[PDB]
């Protein structure tokens, strides 16, 4: 395996891999890490022939109990199951008017200062509409993209690397301590601070920095948080659980 | 030639065809009608394989003199000319963080009573930065998408219909009178009001409603104007000059 890897270089033709989204004032990080990785993998496994932003809105609103409780929290693995069973329609970002069900919860400032309003708690989850937005080419059912398999990847650093290498970005989850909230650059190594919660994300490569091994990770807190929306976190040590809850899945293409 | 046609239904796999953008408080309508139609055509010409949002940002800031004066107004055929000579990078809607160069001018209310700020028009043109956004997969030069030809289409209803039918949506322009500002639905036919100015739009279809033949047009004034951002305008009589300034082009393989 390569000593360094970045899915963005590897499948440069696949623009979703480089995209950072914004979950907004809703606790749907479990949904974002999934549809972000599903988008990447649909493109990767069709060698580029299909490039669709899979809709965070559909997953968040229509998954229901197997996924958790919407904007209050949820379970990554229930998202990948849902996709293999009931699939997910396309959907761009907020006010993009791209695809069937663009996300409806507006961008906000995550533990930073900027132009947009500060994020607040967790707005009620939107209702499941099985209807695409006015304008859109095809019907909601027609627009569904399905998965063929979903699986958990075991806590093995080599297996997770191989899985990213072969098949594209994965979803993961780790424990957030307060000192993460103000990450700017470098390799994050928890030192101080209280427990905040569990946070699901997209892992899209690895590397070394000044001899510290890390995972390259896309957060769902917009591009002005962290290092342009991305962060680096110690790899090889089950640091904050980052190697404990990996899940992925292969598209039906 | 059928008695109706919607590029949205013919090329259901090209989601840009159904997408409404917002030009914001910038007179860049000349650029929007262009890059919307070029995005469409890249998808139609590749059969779905290349599915990018062409940047209104790259065209607006970088074209320079032959397009006109950026946010002050411009010339559609210059746009299509610059596309074939220099090409144009990908670039999503505001805050979409998708593609090389997303749009940097925020959305606003175009003569409607909604929640976003009113457009104050004005707009100073941004500078041309030969550089993608931080996070993007490829370089600015490497991201360029090139036109093979650009051409005008003559004032002939049938030719214009045949051009849309074969090759996809086109850019047009027409004289805007103040009674257009409050269109909601049905086929537009000017009746009263003063002249406001020239307006460049994307034409993507045609049909007949209640005996009246129309063009189906995408405006760049967001989805809350008109009929979900679209509008129909009397066809077959050069109405408001709608059949006089049709410009299009073919993308390079
Ligand atoms: C990440 C996200 O949006 C929500 C809430 O975020 C809390 C938070 C996270 C980071 C920093 C500050 C605050 N979190 C969840 O959806 C988590 C993600 C996955 C956690 N992993 C496991 N194994 N549960 N899921 C979660 O909290 O499930 C519990 C729950 C479900 C339903 C309702 C309440 C709680
Ligand atoms: C449409 C666009 O945003 C601007 C401003 O339009 C003003 C307006 C339109 C409708 C309703 C209210 C206000 N217009 C243009 O960019 C036009 C489009 C081209 C159509 N006709 C032309 N003339 N061939 N271009 C334009 O106005 O060129 C003139 C100009 C160029 C440079 C500087 C000033 C004016």
Image (tube, coloured by chain):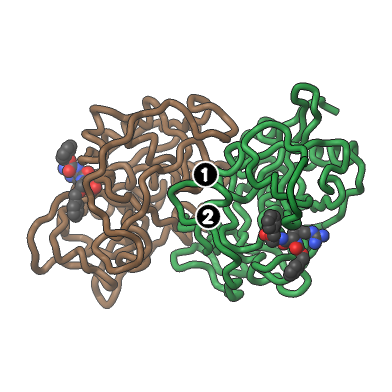
Chain colours: A green, B brown
Task: Tell me whether marks 2 and 1 sit on the same chain.
Answer: no
Residue at horizontal 46 percent and vertical 34 percent from the top? B89
Vertical relation: B78 (above or below) A36: above
Few, some or many residues within 10 Å of mark 1 (<14, 14–19, 20+): many
The chain letter for the residue carrying disc 2 is: A
Q: Which residue is mark 1?
A: B97
Few, some or many residues within 10 Å of mark 2 (<14, 14–19, 20+): many
Q: Secondary structure at mark 2?
A: loop
Q: Are marks 2 and 1 in contact (CB under 8 Å)?
A: yes
Q: Position of residue B72 (x, y in %)?
A: 20, 40
Residue at horizontal 71 percent and vertical 65 percent from the top? A73
Question: Splitting the image into 4 quarters, where does residue A18 fall?
Answer: top right
The disc placed on residue A93 is: 2
Vertical relation: A20 (above or below) B60: below
Q: Position of residue B40 (x, y in %)?
A: 44, 47
Cβ of mark 1 under 8 Å from ligand 1: the answer is no
Cα–Cα gap, marks 2 and 1 = 9 Å
Question: Splitting the image into 4 quarters, where does residue B67 fall?
Answer: top left
The chain letter for the residue carrying disc 1 is: B
Residue at horizontal 73 percent and vertical 48 percent from the top? A193
Residue at horizontal 73 percent and vertical 33 percent from the top? A187
Q: Secondary structure at mark 1?
A: loop
Vertical relation: B88 (above or below) B160: above
């Amino acid at each position: 395996l390569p000593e360094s890897f970045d899915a963005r270089e590897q499948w440069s033709n696949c623009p979703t891999i480089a995209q950072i989204r914004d979950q907004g004032s809703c606790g749907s990080c479990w949904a974002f890490g999934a549809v972000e990785a599903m988008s990447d993998r649909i493109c990767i496994h069709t060698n580029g022939r299909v490039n669709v932003e899979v809709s965070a809105e559909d997953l968040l609103t229509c998954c229901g109990i197997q996924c958790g409780d919407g904007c209050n929290g949820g379970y990554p693995s229930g998202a990948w199951n849902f996709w293999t069973r009931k699939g997910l329609v396309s959907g761009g970002v907020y006010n993009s008017h791209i695809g069937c069900l663009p996300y409806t919860i507006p961008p906000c400032e995550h533990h930073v200062n900027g132009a947009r309003p500060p994020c607040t708690g967790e707005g009620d989850t939107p209702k499941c509409n099985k209807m695409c937005e006015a304008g859109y080419s095809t019907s909601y059912k027609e627009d569904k993209h399905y998965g063929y398999t979903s699986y958990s990847v075991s806590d093995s650093e080599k297996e997770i690397m191989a899985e990213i290498y072969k098949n594209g970005p994965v979803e993961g989850a780790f424990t957030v301590f307060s000192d993460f909230l103000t990450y700017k650059s470098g390799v994050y190594k928890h030192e101080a601070g209280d427990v905040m919660g569990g946070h699901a994300i997209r892992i899209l490569g690895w590397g070394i920095e000044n001899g510290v091994p890390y995972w390259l990770v896309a957060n769902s807190w917009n591009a002005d948080w962290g290092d342009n929306g991305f962060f680096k976190i110690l790899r090889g040590e089950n640091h904050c659980g980052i190697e404990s809850e990996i899940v992925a899945g292969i598209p039906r293409t």
